[PDB]
Image (tube, rainbow over all chains, first blue to last red; front, side):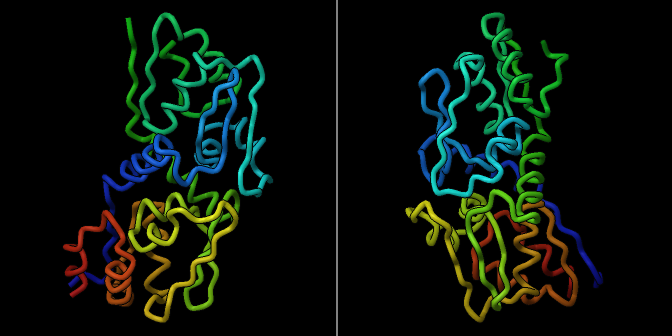
Length: 119
Length: 121
């Protein structure tokens, strides 16, 4: 008997991100390849632009089918891989071994919602 | 010694950033035609939210994709659904509740508790 009802799902945003990470791990429906120290990382250029100002600035305007981005030597796999894991899993795992290299990539890539307090 | 962070708002943050890309027609890769109207979206998101879109997106060419929805799908029933897919929020009223529910079953849109449709009755 209500005139309007505004429905909200508490599980939708989580399932979309789960499907995006599943697409990434299976290399399906991805559109960009990131090169870090020679290693290949498949991803969606939209998700990377969402989580990073650096990726957003290098990707917006590139409308081609497939895109290959090489990050300079200042970016290491030891620092970049925990960040792309956070982008697709919302989980950021730090340790005394990688905290320095991860803190560098957060500032270089300008990853958004990583508070500098956890360092 | 390990420190692990689990953000609960992160999945919401990404989805709201993708919706901002959608509304600005930036970094999209598929055009949806319903009643002739254009709708820009990401095929990765559409495949994650609908079995209808997934079976038409899977294994396609990397180039731009065009998906045309037939006469059953109306803008009055589709626009609240592409909104929901990008916002997790579905605004229902006694006006559009019929065509939206019919469009949910047509596209097989996920994560919509069908119990809420009976509120507009």
